[PDB]
Structure formats: structure tokens, C-alpha cells
Amino acid sequence: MTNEQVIELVRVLLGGITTEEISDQTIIFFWTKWKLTYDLDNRPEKIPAALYNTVVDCVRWLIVQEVSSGNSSIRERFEKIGDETISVKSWESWKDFLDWLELNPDYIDPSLAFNSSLVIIGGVRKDEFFRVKNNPNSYNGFMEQGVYPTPAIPKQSAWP
Amino acid sequence: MTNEQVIELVRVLLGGITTEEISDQTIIFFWTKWKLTYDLDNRPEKIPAALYNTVVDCVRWLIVQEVSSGNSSIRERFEKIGDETISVKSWESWKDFLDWLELNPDYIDPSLAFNSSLVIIGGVRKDEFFRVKNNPNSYNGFMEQGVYPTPAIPKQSAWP
Amino acid sequence: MTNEQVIELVRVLLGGITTEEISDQTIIFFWTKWKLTYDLDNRPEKIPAALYNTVVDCVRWLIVQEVSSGNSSIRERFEKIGDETISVKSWESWKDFLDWLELNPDYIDPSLAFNSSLVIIGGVRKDEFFRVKNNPNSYNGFMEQGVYPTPAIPKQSAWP
Amino acid sequence: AYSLLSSRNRLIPRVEVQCRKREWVKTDPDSPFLNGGREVLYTPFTAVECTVQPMRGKAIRDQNNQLMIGGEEDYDSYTVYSETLLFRAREGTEHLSDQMLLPDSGGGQTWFTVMKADMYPSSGVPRYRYYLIAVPVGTEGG
Amino acid sequence: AYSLLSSRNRLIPRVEVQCRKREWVKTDPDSPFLNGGREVLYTPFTAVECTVQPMRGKAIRDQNNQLMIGGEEDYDSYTVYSETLLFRAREGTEHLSDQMLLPDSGGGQTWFTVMKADMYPSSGVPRYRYYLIAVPVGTEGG
Amino acid sequence: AYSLLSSRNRLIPRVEVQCRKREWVKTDPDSPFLNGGREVLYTPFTAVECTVQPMRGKAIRDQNNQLMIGGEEDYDSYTVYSETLLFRAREGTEHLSDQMLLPDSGGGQTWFTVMKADMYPSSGVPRYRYYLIAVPVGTEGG
């Protein structure tokens, strides 16, 4: 993806967010950070992964933007300069959205292979059995040397 | 990293915090603290580590800035010098952000190797098994001398 | 550390606290107290320890400063001398900060060796085993004399 | 000291208005009078932010068009809250009262002359209240 | 800026009313007077939505039928809130005050002449308040 | 007895003001009159802490600049809350009313003369209210 498409895509995904709420320079800053770490030009397979992380970081910057200003710590207002009176009572709204977004990554890109390896059962596949068995660093139960080593007990996991 | 980029990077990460809220002097003070403890010039492998501690320390100084002033202990205000009336009601917001930031270090630098060694199981690796076994200071169960020492029981952990 | 650096360091750590909130004389009073007890001039290894305790004592003096005055026991105010009305409703804020500070001593000095000996397991080190075994004052299970003493039971913990 | 009122509001909209200072001068060379042929000198300026409101009642002297023996004359007034300092006339001097341009009931724009200014010297915050009366139609006031 | 007041209400019913603009013209060919034989020209129109309310007190000048040496004369008035702009008379011109037709205490319908118009130039929302007086019975006002 | 009001406030800012006492004396050696050539003697002092506020209405006599047949005269007034005792004039004596210096609508500073003083003898706390009127421009009052 080029530098101009990312701002176009992020703004649409964030419900048409405006420039003052989030500048185009900040989006490039997070976009560039994941470009150098994932060398997207070298391997184009990380386009969905780099795109998903970029949006999440932008939401994080939005939350901290409410902080460091007076918006986060106020929950009341009252103006009265005569006959005009106004009283109203997004920091908390951005919170659960970030939690919700991390649970539905398909909203960004459906090809993220999300939710595929929840349950793992060991010893029910030949591919997984031999990979563990043939690992030279593996130490299993058949290596119990006891008091002092004896040649009756194997020193390697793999079968001869 | 040089003395000027740290301020530029910190402000962007903190959502464009202003100069009056945190001076550039205080940022250097915490930046210099970790430079001498991690000799960044001698070993550049600690650039992410020094950067992470610098940002966290700045947030800590921000929290104590609300304390030691009237901002922390007040939760109401009311002004009236005639017809003008105003009533409104960051110490609490900066608290949870520090807790959140301590749980998401990837927001600062993805290369921090966060969350990699949660679960440890002993005796399932040859590298770790021999490290403990060959340790001259190790004392294991096969050394139970009893009432008085006997030459039938080893005095060293490593096998001959 | 000299007498002038400590005030400079404490004020920065406390978020730029002012002179009226805490005088420079009180800081010296607590600084001097830990100097004579830890003879910093004799052993410069206690610079972090004396510095950490000095800041904690200052926070304690800040809490008791809210007490012994009207600030602690009031939670309302109302002034009305005509058209000017003001109504607002740090003793409790300094409380949890002292609790928080005692849990994060690295904020003062990272070289305090904090959080290093939480879990202790006995009998798994030769250094710890022989120190207890060779202690002349130690009394273990192999000394059970029973009804009256007999020469079949050792009177010293260390092996011959 | 006051803190909240020492800063600009953030709920009620405020606007800026234009104003102009006023002096006077004698022109006749031989007339023995201080009046002479009076002239007024102007120097424009603006108010930082202001709020305009109309009179609250319906008293006969506060109505807009008034019936006189000549014809249906015109009248307007306002109450203004502002953070700029405006001055009335001072005696034994050549300074006149400040004026500021505001919309009227006839759809046009006309000059209003400051008549009453309220200040709170002991409070400190720079917030003022003014009362204004529209200049007679066809003239520049006095 | 104001948002809620910048939109039409949805709880209190509002109605539209009819109005008419007014000018005047000289007809006499030889009379040297600006008056001449005065005539008034009308151009009708309507107000988008309005609310009509009566005077609140019972003062002697606000009563409907009044006893004069000739006979029991007639009088009526109202206070109107509207989102249409109506203008009063302006001097040195040929424009007169707008009028609008409303029901009266006698069961009929008569024209009311705008006398006082209130505006808030610094707020922005187009909401106005007017004060109206019924035209004398048997004439078209002035 | 009152406790809270018997102590200085800690929310609303208060300021100190300057004042001056006033007597009078006869100067003419041969004139048979008590007036003679009257003179006033002053002795300055200050008020511990005070609050100044302006008149609340817009009545014609409370406006700042007033139109008279001579020229646009000047007028100002205030209401003051203070913890210092100030005295009015007393008859059959040579004492006059105290005065105190405050800012005016023209940007300068002028003397105000005490006209009404309010006290609560049965309460005990020393809190007073005063009403002041600016001295005529170009003179020192009476």
C-alpha cells in the first residue's frame, strides 16, 4: 500500500474521522513504524498484519489525546453570560471500542486467520509427534538416569 | 538517539503534550538517568529499554504534578462576579493510563521482547537440565548424608 | 551528595513542589537524620538508601501538615460578600501516593535492588546448607536426648 | 482569587464587534467660542468578544418605532457584555463617548453610544457590562 | 454554538400566520407636500411558524373594551414568537411597519401592527419576539 | 454568638482602599459668619479590606454620562462592604463625611463620599455596608 491509501482507508474504518481529531502526520508515523519492522516491500504477505496494527495504535493515540487535556477530567459545564445558558454533562467511549476492536479483527481485514488455534491436543498427530520426538534438545521420561548413568537408558530422544 | 529526538518522540507518544505541562528539561533529566545506568553509547541494544523507562518515568512525574497542587483535591468550582457564572467538575485519568501503559509496551517499541517467558516447566530441556546439574553450588536430593557422612554418597552434583 | 543537591533532587521528584508547601529547612532535617545513622561520608554505598528514606519522610511530613490545620477536616466552602460567590468541595491524595511510592522505589533510584528475594527455598544450596549446619548455636533433630543424655547422640551440629 | 471567570468561555458563543473613539475640535478662526464649528475625530478599533441582548420589558419608551407629531420616529437599545474596556465622556476634556456598530430592528446597521459602564475594581477579572442607545437617525450623536 | 435552538420544536404546537408589507406614495399632482394624497401599497406573505399569547396583567390600558366620552371603544394586543424576520418603519424612506392578521376578542379577525422587535445578533439562531397592537377599528393604521 | 462571620473570608478576594477624614474651619477674620472662608482639613487612612460593586439597574439617574443644557456631565456610584468603621457628618460639629478613592468609568480615579452606612448593633460582628456617590468633577464635595 502507498502512503496516500492508508489515510484514506483508516479514516473510512474509523467512521469518517476528521483531520483535527487525528492528523495525517500521526497516521504516517504509526504506518512507517510497522513498515520498517515488517519490511512490507520485501514480503507483501504482511499487508493485513501491518494494517491491523496501524489502526490499533491510532486508537491508542486517540485515547491518550483525551488525556493530557481538560476533556478527560471534566464531566460538567455551565456557561451563563446573560440570557444564554448552556449545560452538558469520548475518553471512555474510545476505551471499550479498543477492547471490542481487538476481538473483531475481521472488520479491518478478513484474511487475518483469526481464531484458528484455540484448542490444542497433543499426541494425536504424526507431524506433531515426530517433531517433538526428533528434537535434539528434547528431554522425556525415558531418560531417568537415577543414581548414576547406565548404558541401559537412552541419551537421545530420537529412535535409532 | 540524540538529546533532541527524545523530546520529539515522547511528545508524539503522549498525544502531543504541551510544553507547560511537561518541560523539556524534565524529559532530559529522566533520559540522562537511564543513559548512565545503561551506557547506551557503549551498548546500543538498550535503546528500546531506555526509551520505555523514560516514558514511564515522565508519566510518574506527571501524576505527582497534579499532587502538590490544588488540582488533585478539588472536585467542584463556582465563579460569579456578576452575571457571569461558571461551574465545572487529570490525577485520576493519569493513574489508569500508567497501569495500561505498563501492560502494553509494544505501543512504544515492538522490539521489547514482551510476554515471552510466562510458563516455565523444568526438566524438559537438555540445556537447562545440564545447567543445574553441572552447577558446583547445586545441592540435590542425592546428597542426603544422614547422621554422619559416608563415602557411599556423592558430594558433588555433576556426574564423574 | 551535598546539602544543595538534595533539595534540587527532592523538588523535581515531587513534581516541582514549592517552598511554602515544604521548606528547605525541613528537607535538611530529614536528610541530616539519615546521614548520621548511615555515615554516608564513611560508606558511599548508602547514597540510594538514604535518598529513598529522605523522600518518604518528607511525604510523611506533608500528610501531617494537612493535619494540625483546618484543611483536613473541611470538605465544603461558601463565600458570599455580595455578587461574588465561590463554592468548592490534599490529605487523602498524599495517602495513596505514599502507599504507591513504597511499592515503586525505582522511581527514586533504580539501583536499590528492590524485589529480589521474594521466594526462599531451603536445603537446595550448599552455601545455605553448610552455614546452618556449621552454626554452633544450631539445634536440629539429631540431638533428641530423650530421658537422660547418652553418648550415642551428638551434642554439636557440625560433622566431625 | 477568581480563576474560572478569568478565562474565556467555552459553551456560549461570543462575537467581536467594531468600535471607534471620538474627540472634538474647534474650527472657526475668529469665533470667540469654545464650540466654534465643532468637528469629531475618529479612530477605529474592535472588541475582543461580546454578547448583545435586547431590552427585556415593553415600556413605552423602549418600543422601536414611536409616534410623534412629526412622524414615526426610530429607537433602539441593547445590553452588552464584553472583555474590552470602553470609556464614556469626561468633562473638561476633548474626549467623547465611544461608539460601536450593531444591527438594528430595521435590518440595517447603525452606531450605538455607550451610556453606562459597570466595573468591579475589587475582583480583578476583566469582565464588563455596558448599556447602549442607538444614535438618532441622520446624525452622529453628541 | 447553539444546536438545539437552531431547529424547530417538537413538543409545543406552532402555527403559521399571514402578513403584508406596507409602503406609501404621493398622489396629488399639484400639492407641494410630501404627504399629498397618501396611499399604501401591500405585498402579502406568511410567517413560517409562530406562537401567539395575550397580555399578562389587567392594567386599565390593556383592557379590551374601553369607555370614552364617545362610546365603548376597542383595543387588543399580543406577544408573538416567530422564526420569520419582520421589520418596523424606517425614517427617510417610504417603508412602513409590517402587519399580520390574527383573531380578536370580538370573534372576528383584524390586522396587528408590529411595534417592537427583539433580536440577538451575537447568538446566531433565528428566533425573534414581537409585540403587536391591533389597528384602530375602521382604519388601516399609520 | 456568631463565629464564622467574625473572621476574614477565604474564598472571595478582597482589597484595601484609601480614605481621608474631613473637617472644616473659618478663615475670615472680620466676617460675622460661621461660614467665613471655609476650609477643609484632611487626615488620610486606609480600610482593612473592602469589596466594590456597581449599581444594579439602569435608571436614568444611575447612568454615567448625563445630558444637561450645559454639556455631558458625569456621575458614578458604588456599593461597598467593609470591615472598617466610616462615619457620616454630624450636626452642630465641625466634622464632615469620610471619603475614599476608587476607580471610575472614565479610566481615572476620584473621591467618593459616604452617604449611607449600615450597622447591626445587636449582632456584634464588625461587618458594614456603605453607599457612595462620586464627588462632582472639579470640586471637593461638601
Image: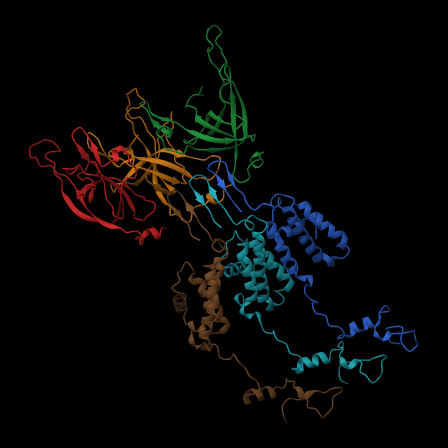
Chain colours: A brown, B cyan, C blue, D orange, E red, F green
Q: Is residue F6 above or below residue A154?
A: above
**Residue C92 rendering spot, x and y as whole percentages:** 60, 51
The image quadrant that residue C74 belongs to is top right
Q: Along the line of sight, which residue is nearer the eye, F118 or C1? A: F118
Residue E128 is left or right of residue A9, and the answer is left
**Residue D32 rendering spot, x and y as whole percentages:** 30, 19
**Is residue E37 in sight in this rendering?**
yes
**Is residue A134 in sight in this rendering?**
no
Quadrant assignment for the C terminus of chain B: bottom right
Q: Residue at x 43, y 26 (%)?
A: F134
Q: Along the line of sight, which residue is nearer the eye, D25 or B61? A: B61
Q: Along the line of sight, which residue is nearer the eye, E80 or E45? A: E80
Q: Residue furthest bottom?
A: A160
Q: Residue furthest left?
A: E30
**Residue D103 rendering spot, x and y as whole percentages:** 29, 41
Quadrant assignment for the N terminus of chain B: bottom right
Residue E101 is left or right of residue A49, and the answer is left
Residue A105 is left or right of residue D98, and the answer is right
Q: Along the line of sight, which residue is nearer the eye, B142 or B39? A: B142
**Residue F8 rendering spot, x and y as whole percentages:** 56, 35
The image quadrant that residue B26 belongs to is bottom right
Q: Residue at x 32, y 52 (%)?
A: E6
Looking at the rendered structure, the number of numbered marks drawn on it comes to: 0
